[PDB]
Length: 171
Length: 170
Image (cartoon, rainbow over all chains, first blue to last red; front, side, top):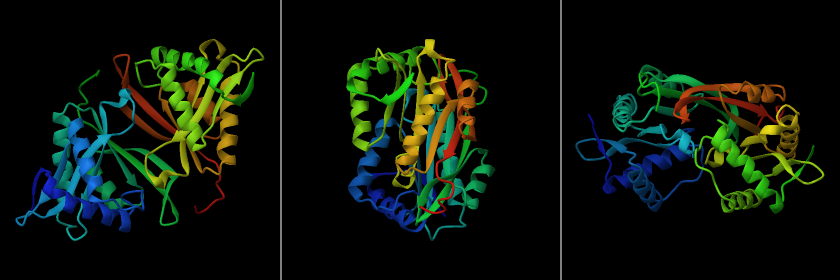
């Protein structure tokens, strides 16, 4: 069982581990270079400055079982109503619905912040991640062949999105 | 018009085109004009990365249009992919300068050993979508209301061209 809450500085070591595990063992991050704590501390502060949340799923021991966050999608003012999010569940916490918990909480935050669209960039072969998003209302909006690479092979990218306030006809 | 690499002397002309697009089109999703310094820094950033900036020019050396490309997404895994842009001065539209510029860019990207060129086009811009389609680009995404300008929501269409289809692995 896990509770969803805002991340604090003491959560960074845990977040760092999950981040680096994904970097080394998955196609969730299209980087093969692990980062250090200072890197995550800078990221932590940068998110706060933009008013973007960093959420963690923590257990009784206070261990970080997963985390989620979102930030700018494209670097132009025209996209200020759109954010790209990410969800990472610890390798030993799969099948426990933590991904759903985190994304649902993240969606509520994004909507409350007055954002218009959330975009997910998912390695196309990741059926589980795509399925989780589909179940939460996200629709496929991009399918790009060989735009990336990792582990010495080309990777395809799938874009999915959720309109947080479809009844708002204009910004 | 002839295509050539941009020089510092071309920045004022590029600036005018850029700011015209900022205030009049959906080609640039920003509503604030930039200054010469801004485009000089952009010019230098490109040169630093080895990325080209081409201009369509006449004998008088006037900038009739320009094109360039840079990183698409900020992760090493996308190093084989670049996002490009093509801008034709308003009065020079309908003269094939866009085709000239994009063709030149494509050849440059291929010669640089790049793998994929990505175009992010405002969905209602059929002219731009057609230009790309006729040069081998394929639609790869339709993202509604992900942008905004002129007080309205804008849709983004993604298109892409694989520069080396036979290269099965990086």
